[PDB]
Image (cartoon, rainbow, N blue to C red; front, top):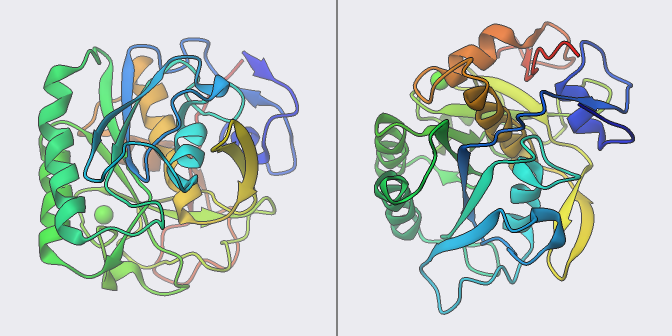
Length: 279
Ligand SMILES: [Ca+2]
């Protein structure tokens, strides 16, 4: 299935080269998979979600996304126009307030929530969680991400936007989850993207068009934007069978475009998420 004039990041994920604008993907499109977006929430009413999104948890006075960030990330995972996995089910977990902030204790509670909550959902092809958030190193935050992964969820987390080694950030520094750096449309490491040994993969992160609150759309940049490309990719590959929650990060690394990114520091993987779809 070809989507013409797709956002550059979608086109990139199904291409052996930069500079194209059509996204190619198997029509199964993540059907039967689920992706949790642990963030500021998701505007489920957005026409782009087609009824496939819903809020399942909040730690605040509302489950509404009053920020937009969570809605944008969810759109990159699974919206009809802006999403990687256009038929996945999206579950919003609001651990961040409308200012985009959240206490680590609330974020941890949200991760443990997902590990249990998946047992209340129908996800026969598998379960993914996208965590476009982070802060300074915390063993407790890392451990929560590790538990979520251990429980049978493909956990994708943002490397961070500090142009620094991600070893000093959490959950980025957790070895057992999939830590995602950001690239731009010219295959350069995004200027803000963290790097380091803890990174597992890069995805499109600069100038990413997706859904926004109030039924709108906008382009923003961050490792927050790269992460949902990888989460959506995992969901897509899981419905194809190709991989499982426990092996998806390795599989994505195995099958990535290799050595094609510029300004990757010595010691950081040079791997760009790729669906290996042959139309
Ligand atoms: Ca790792």
